[PDB]
């Protein structure tokens, strides 16, 4: 398998630490039925959580993860809900009183967020604000925000919104409501990503569409990223912006060729179709030489400064009505180059 | 495959009527990346729409239908959006000025809507209200509501919510804003449905889980339901509640058995697991012997009277506040018998 070949296989997976962190917890996962959310769900059950509240706005995604976990049906509750519905979300948190929220709900596609920036802002930033505020109000002990390497020096709407969500959640962190964010890169075979695209092109005898001959990405398996996110949540004391190490980058052309080789399909061409708007060619330096080490060699802590929430709330209000979203996002993230 | 077997293959598919109806139109499809919406999008391009506005809240579903239609990308615009965001929907409608809205966005699962009746109400009823209101205000000429046979004498929250959407949209119909609803039954192989569930159980060496040995459903292919919906929309003058003829119902036990026979896994057990809450054994009579015929033999018009919108709007507000959704729904839909 191509997944197998590019797997990170990190040597510092710690089952026992995740078990101790999750034992008998009521846990709520937003985006429960997504690529990452579904794997969080599965690992929460595997590592002994008492009760899993699965929140997703996509009815098929929710149905599917509920169905996948049907052997544990007594321990899970499928909540069909947008996190933008504050009043319903508050009712959910007061009812179940989760001690941990794993926030994986977001819009993540670079091109679609470029084309729909307002919805990106609303779903990502406002949805994060609503979920985060509700968690703090409802005395959730720990809140882990799934973030992305795309939030570093963002060149696109999606990335920028995720950076704003880091700023917001980390600024809400305190002794009673401990927030951690976890940045990582491309999850192998995730929803709507390049591996399923190539797989489908091959199966339909189409040429593979490669954006640029020199483009590279960092990859890991969903089970690896999720477990490390959970180990990061487990060691968090509140306020940490974590980042995962992912090994060496992989050329997408090499990925394309390996896929072709694995299906004995060297009858097919690889066609250059050009960079998509917002897209980086090399991403960013993963780990700064001065990020703090943790006890896990795959997990580092990056520097982050709280921001004045009053100011941030004003900017977020403006984001929901303003005419130029890109320019507005810049006033919040001055490193944003769109 | 199982789909082949149970196809309807109506004799009265009419490409040309659909082509004439869709020619050069700007068409907005809500729920565009769903099972039915995706097929609506494809048929809109096939039959010569000018421009397709694809609205969906699931980024993956939208991504996928957008990619599926890559060959025709200059004719399609992917709008990542919940129809509950009135202000943004309004802006989309003003920017693109669609002439036709095909409304396929909803929550459709009996059990999930049983378990989340408030979100069923919000996403189905309020989402329909917002989209329908915005369409009329923005002078969209024709609005087609995808409905369901479950709206008839509903026994579950989902079906009841769909019936309220019928009442709302049809009561908004007038000479400028023509509304049709179309009711039909199970679409073979649709998202989250019994066929994909049985396929996975088989692929995983699991017993098939059959709710009840006697349960039956009416089935048709997505391409058939969709084209018939488009033909209904083509002949509509406003205010019609259409219903499709779907042929003979199918015992789910016979569908299970046939799946096991086709993959040669008669080694697997069929386990009876019990009816799910809200579920009917035999659905309902499809075509009332008095429903009116149309020019197509697969499409009929079911009786329906407008309700006062003043009344309905206030009942819809009550739905968003009440203690007890089921009781509140019964006020609007007095034939609702909630299992
Ligand atoms: N997939 C990757 O390669 C990758 C890499 C780094 C970070 N991330 C981050 O992980 C998070 C999840 O990514 P994914 O691959 O699982 O995407 P995904 O789209 O498969 O899953 C996201 C889930 O959230 C749900 N959702 C979205 N908005 C919602 C809302 N308002 N209310 C409730 N549910 C909502 C979706 O329906 C979906 O099931 C996103 O920020 C993403 O940016 C992903
Ligand atoms: N599948 C069947 O058997 C069947 C039979 C009869 C009627 N119907 C009706 O057909 C319609 C679609 O069913 P389907 O099988 O395609 O289901 P689906 O879930 O596959 O498709 C619905 C689509 O609507 C989207 N959506 C839901 N709420 C939304 C919102 N608030 N804003 C924007 N997008 C939203 C979803 O993301 C999804 O892509 C529903 O109206 C259902 O009520 C289905
Ligand atoms: C999963 C998804 O949809 N996007 C995520 C993905 O972004 P990213 O945009 O990298 O995800 P993709 O899987 O879409 O693309 C992976 C790589 O393949 C290339 N490519 C893509 C499609 C194609 O047809 N041909 C082609 O060559 C891209 O240019 C990119 O170099 O990882 C980032 C982490 O680093 C996250 O921030 C994004 O949320
Ligand atoms: C998920 C879905 O598309 N639901 C639609 C489906 O409902 P419906 O609930 O009939 O659709 P499903 O495919 O879930 O179920 C079909 C039949 O198979 C049975 N079954 C299902 C699952 C299983 O594990 N075992 C089993 O035996 C059910 O009891 C039912 O008799 O068609 C109706 C139209 O008639 C629509 O109103 C619903 O929106
Ligand atoms: Na899966
Ligand atoms: Na359960
Ligand atoms: Na499809
Ligand atoms: Na396009």
Image (cartoon, coloured by chain):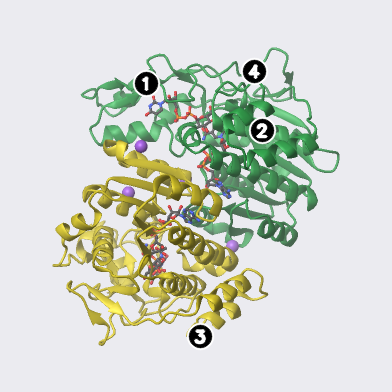
Chain colours: A green, B yellow
Q: Which residue is mark 4?
A: A287
Q: Chain of mark 2?
A: A
Q: Which residue is mark 2?
A: A164
Task: Farthest residue to the right: give it.
Answer: A175
Q: Is residue A232 visible?
A: no
Q: Nearer the viewer, residue A55 or B1?
A: A55
- The crowding category of the residue bearing disc 1, from other C-alpha atoms within 10 Å (few below 14, some 14 to 19, many at least 20), is few
Q: Secondary structure at mark 4?
A: loop
Task: Tell me if label 4 and label 3 are in contact, CB under 8 Å.
Answer: no
The residue that appears at 39% across and 61% down in the rendered structure is B193
User: Mark 1 or mark 4, which is nearer the start of the sequence?
Assistant: 1
Q: Are the residues under marks 4 and 2 on the same chain?
A: yes
Task: Tell me if label 2 and label 1 are in contact, CB under 8 Å.
Answer: no
Q: Are the residues under marks 4 and 3 on the same chain?
A: no
> What quarter of the picture does the N terminus of chain A occupy?
top left
Q: Quick check: A33 left or right of B293?
A: right
């Amino acid at each position: 398998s191509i997944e197998d070949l590019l797997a990170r296989k990190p040597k510092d997976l710690d089952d026992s630490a995740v078990a101790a962190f999750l034992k008998d917890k009521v846990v709520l996962v937003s985006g429960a039925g997504g690529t990452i959310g579904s794997e969080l769900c599965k690992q929460c059950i595997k590592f002994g959580a008492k009760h899993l509240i699965m929140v997703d706005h996509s009815e098929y995604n929710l149905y599917k993860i509920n169905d996948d976990l049907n052997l544990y049906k007594e321990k899970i509750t499928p909540i069909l809900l947008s996190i933008l519905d504050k009043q319903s979300l508050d009712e959910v948190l007061k009812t179940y009183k989760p001690e941990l929220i794993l926030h994986a709900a977001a819009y993540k596609h670079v091109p679609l967020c470029e084309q729909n920036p307002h919805s990106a802002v609303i779903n990502n930033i406002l949805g994060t604000k609503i979920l985060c505020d509700s968690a703090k109000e409802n005395k959730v002990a720990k809140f882990v925000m799934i973030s992305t390497n795309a939030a570093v020096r963002p060149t696109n709407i999606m990335g920028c919104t995720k950076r704003v969500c880091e700023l917001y959640t980390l600024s809400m962190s305190d002794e009673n409501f401990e927030v951690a964010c976890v940045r990582f890169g491309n999850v192998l075979g995730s929803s709507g990503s390049v591996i399923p695209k190539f797989k489908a092109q091959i199966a339909n005898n189409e040429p593979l569409t490669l954006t640029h001959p020199d483009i590279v990405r960092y990859f890991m398996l969903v089970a690896e990223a999720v477990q490390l996110v959970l180990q990061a949540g487990a060691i968090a004391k509140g306020g940490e912006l974590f980042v995962l190490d992912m090994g060496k980058p992989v050329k997408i052309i090499d990925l394309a060729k390996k896929m072709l080789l694995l299906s004995n399909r060297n009858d097919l061409e690889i066609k250059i179709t050009g960079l998509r708007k917002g897209e980086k060619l090399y991403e960013e330096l993963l780990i700064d030489e001065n990020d703090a080490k943790t006890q896990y060699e795959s997990i580092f802590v990056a520097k982050n400064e709280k921001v004045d929430l009053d100011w941030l709330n004003k900017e977020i209000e403006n984001l929901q009505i303003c005419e130029d979203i890109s320019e507005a996002l810049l006033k919040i993230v001055p490193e944003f180059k769109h």
